[PDB]
Length: 154
Length: 152
Image (cartoon, rainbow over all chains, first blue to last red; front, side):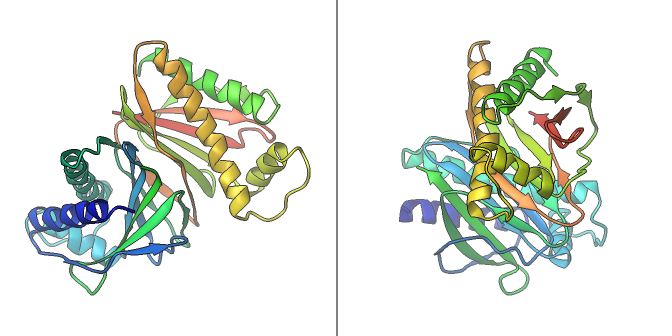
């Protein structure tokens, strides 16, 4: 996969979780993986079409979901994964793909971002297609966001 | 939601769950829902961009899944749900969305399709965004496939 892409992703995650959560993230080291293990119970999926067709998938614990939402809410404490709570997460990732989309444009990659689809369950397993990039991310805890970027084509 | 779309969807599903699986299915009755109530454990999610922004979410069971595989793999037998089985499952949803897209093209709207993502779990709950259309499908069992098309 193109480092430009990998970099384009990194910047989007960095800039985004800084403006929305107000905290500077710690991007980890890029890494190709064969499948996707979800240790959590909350997973979001965002499609991408065009220059590159695949996806952006990120998940995390319920405890982290809260700190996340509470952060988007300016500071208001929180502890209830209501409907808006799911929208919070969905909004976070959407804004991310939103920035990733713009950055790919500059480099000449015209892609379109799909709305998010937030899934939550117990023993979760996902099956994506294309080459799976893994980007380690530390927001509040050490690596509390295990994000992936699939590229079927592009 | 533009019935001209539900139109392209049910026909797409129909014409696809028909040629790929060789069986004509019964499309239930189009419903409008406030959210997606997941009655199964395996979902196939496919996204739409362009003319419309939304998704296509097939919901089916593990049992229902292997019957699709066998129905695709020349009708032989299939017991485990391994990667191949999975890739088959996606292609089916993918071939559908592909036809939905193709029908959309002829009515003005230009849309692009995302590759599918199969997810599975205990106590599933999918949060979707936008307006939603529910369409029940019966292939083998009665309503063994519940599909949702959330939009813009």
